[PDB]
Amino acid sequence: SNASAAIYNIDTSSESPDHYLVDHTLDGRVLFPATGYLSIVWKTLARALGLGVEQLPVVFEDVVLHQATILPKTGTVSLEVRLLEASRAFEVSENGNLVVSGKVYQWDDPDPRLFDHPELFLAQAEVYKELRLRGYDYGPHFQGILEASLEGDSGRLLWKDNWVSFMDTMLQMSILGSAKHGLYLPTRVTAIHIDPATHRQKLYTLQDKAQVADVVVSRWLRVTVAGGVHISGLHTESAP
């Protein structure tokens, strides 16, 4: 089988292009987001195919997050992505330790219907007050929920050409309508489908020139859907 690999050096200090990750700090620890792993794996697959990420509709299956990755406040940590073609597998490691595994492959015939649904709101500040009370201290670059219903099953997400923070605000919504008390971190995701062509068509502009997308959470189907992203079967565990 063919194999491919790429190494991403993550620096969060004040002059780094990845300084925005300091706004993903949970109970005082800077944690690399689960959706940051999705992003670097997707980039590695595009790089292996000679495509841009926006040209690559993609499926993830059976994503398992084996441990959290703390980020350093100075210097760098290096995350390595390896892909194996025949099995469609990927692995992410850090200093030889396995961090994430699963399957990833191009979505050969995307179905735009996956991103549609049949057809009392909290403002942004109250949303992040609610998340703060539940234990999540997101800073401004991760405050992408612009409004959400009191039940947490619909809302609007900001789009800033950043797939990491956009998909993280989809996980934030799922947490919003939860009966769980306290801080919970992802441990696995059954499937993720991304179609950038649909994403571009789902975006719309508010009066303030902000590009946004509608988000819904289905308790019945165990899915969260926004723009061109469909997340199925999220599971989480308690953290201190």
Image (spheres, rainbow, N blue to C red):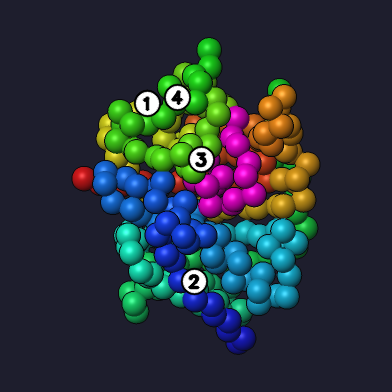
Where's residue 60, x and y in %? 57, 59
Q: Which residue is mark 2?
A: 8
Q: Name which residue type carries label 1.
A: Glu
Q: Residue at x 71, y 52 (%)?
A: 195
- Relative placement, left or right, of 149 versus 69 is right
Residue 125 circle label: 4
**Is 90 above or below relative to 209?**
below
Of residues 184 and 234, the one drawn nearer to the viewer in this rendering: 184
User: Of the residues under marks 1 and 2, which one precedes in the sequence?
Assistant: 2
Where's residue 81, x and y in %? 50, 74
Residue 169 circle label: 3
Q: Which residue is mark 1?
A: 130
In terms of secondary structure, where does tag 4 sit?
helix
Of residues 159 and 170, the one drawn nearer to the viewer in this rendering: 159
The span shown in magenta is 156-170
Q: Residue at x 66, y 60 (%)?
A: 58
Q: Which quadrant holds the C terminus?
A: top left
